[PDB]
Image (cartoon, rainbow, N blue to C red):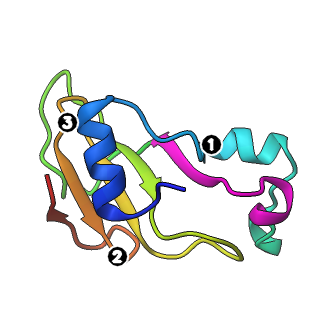
Amino acid sequence: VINTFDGVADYLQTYHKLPDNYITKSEAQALGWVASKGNLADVAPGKSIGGDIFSNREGKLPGKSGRTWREADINYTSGFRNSDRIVYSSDWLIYKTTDHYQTFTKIR
């Protein structure tokens, strides 16, 4: 699967889309994912959550009109979601967070 910072960052700026192992939260729930039981890997084998819009209300990510932030989970294999996310924009800017969106650093 493609689910590393560099792998997803590079796929995204190229293909302008997420790798095929990503599914949205509502998609995952439709299949039976229940966040409380950390069972993603049981109902959606080899899938990661990714593609949901990140609103950016604590203004920490660079704002602009026409720009939309989207997030994807990084390094997940199974169990409960980790704290790693890739935050990507409409204009292909790429940021990462390894602390549940407290702090962000630019990667692309």
| Residue 23 badge | 1
* Residue 34 falls inside the magenta stretch: no
Give me the residue at 66% from left, 53% from top. Answer: 47
The amino acid type found where label 3 is placed reads Trp
The amino acid type found where label 1 is placed reads Ile
Image position, residue 85 (x, y; %) = 39, 63
The answer to whether residue 89 is above or below residue 38 is above
What are the residue bounds of the magenta stretch? 40-52
Sequence-first disc among 3 and 2: 3
Image position, residue 18 (x, y; %) = 44, 38
Label 1 element class: strand
Instruction: Quote the CA–CA distance across marks 3 and 2.
Output: 20 Å
Label 2 element class: loop
Give me the residue at 69% from left, 73% from top. Answer: 78
Sequence-first disc among 3 and 1: 1
The residue most toward the top is 66
* Residue 50 falls inside the magenta stretch: yes
Residue 84, quarter of the rendered image: bottom left
Q: Is residue 33 left or right of residue 49?
A: right
The answer to whether residue 17 is above or below residue 54 is above
Image position, residue 99 (x, y; %) = 36, 78
Q: Is residue 66 left or right of residue 78?
A: left
Look at mark 2 in the image and give the residue it sits on: 98
Q: Residues within 10 Å of mark 3 (few under 14, many from 20)?
A: some
Look at mark 3 in the image and give the residue it sits on: 92
Sequence-first disc among 2 and 1: 1
> Observer-nearest residue: 68 or 96?
96
The answer to whether residue 78 is above or below residue 41 is below
Label 3 element class: loop
The amino acid type found where label 2 is placed reads Thr
The residue most toward the front is 1
Instruction: Quote the CA–CA distance across marks 3 and 1.
Output: 20 Å
